Image (cartoon, each protein chain N blue to C red):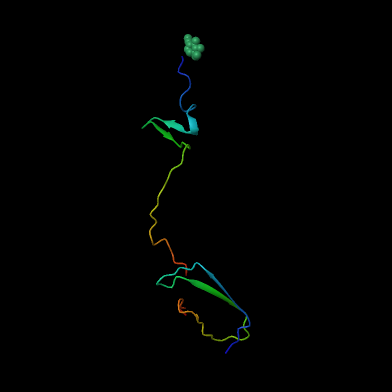
Length: 48
Length: 49
Ligand SMILES: *[C@@H]1O[C@H](CO)[C@@H](O)[C@H](O)[C@H]1NC(C)=O
């Protein structure tokens, strides 16, 4: 009777709830610091 | 020897290093096709070619 509405229609930041491992998918809320160790094979010299 | 009527040196992405880290482009409007010696007149920078 009084379940209200599920988190598939209530959860903030516009992300959808699934139940097989119970995960919240595609939540766009914060900022992620990231560090990449690009290999030297990608870099080419300024001459080429 | 061909005569260079005008020449302009523009250099981008210079790196002072043991390797040849700098590259400069000479724009020229000479009068005849031929071979020139290119030289750097400083004791601090040396040309590869
Ligand atoms: C069950 O839930 C609804 C939803 O609010 C409620 O209005 C209703 O009175 C409840 N009972 C029945 C018998 O439907």
